[PDB]
Every structure is written in structure tokens, then in C-alpha cells.
Image (cartoon, rainbow, N blue to C red; front, side, top):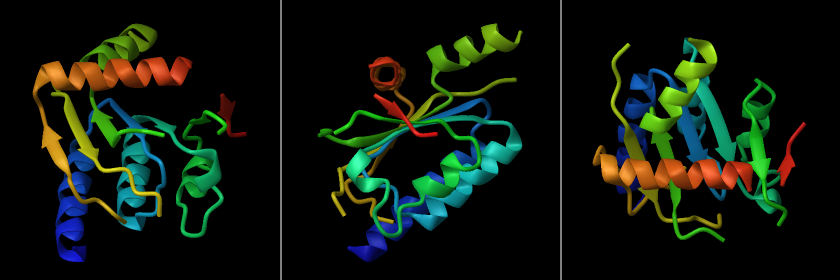
Length: 151
């Protein structure tokens, strides 16, 4: 229900607000203005953000991916199915990666939800279990390396 979704989105925005180093987001469609703005604020905070999404859904109405890509957020797209959408905040491997390329404490958080083909965030799970955050982060690294990267 809309209520459960709003509560879930609110919890996610809170995690985004706490992001220190990185946010990796794999999502089929991005329609949440609230989620986007939180990500926008993270970007302004110095957080490194990457987005993987679907080509059919980036030019859909209410798609917020357009404005994030305009701000410099790299968006990679397969052209042209996921078991779930997910967000990894400060993944261990990713933070260590950033640390090397650039020479503060944090803790990995993965948010996952059901894929919506048309913000909507039911079946939401938020966890810091490092085994899970690792598999998701590793999975993102793989998908990122594979693919259209939006100009």
C-alpha cells in the first residue's frame, strides 16, 4: 500500500543521508522525487554515485534519472530483467576502491526492493549484513563492467 511505500522510502532517504563515500543504485525505474533529491544531496555532500537502469524506462514520464545524469551521475544501461532493485551505500569493496583512487568510518548498507515496471518501494529490505552487502556490491561491479552510458 501507498502508506507502506512512503514509510519505506522515508527509511531509505535516511540511509542515503548518512552515506559517506558511495551510493551504487541498480533500479528498473526511478520515479521517486524524494529518493532522487536525497541522492542529489549526497552528490552535493561529495558522495560518489553510480546508477544502473533500464533503457526503456529512462525516458518514461516521471523518470528522475534524467535530472541526476544532468548533474554528472554516471548512468549505465544494458540495452535492452532483474530479480530485485537494490541500493548499496558505502559497500566495503567500493569504499576501499575509492580510497585507492583518491588516497572516515562507515558501514555498508544494502536496500533491496521488488522491481516495479511502473515512488514505489514495497517488499523493502534494509540490512547491514556484510555477507549480503558484499554479494550485492560485487554484483553491481559486475553489471557496471558488463552497454550504453548516457551522455
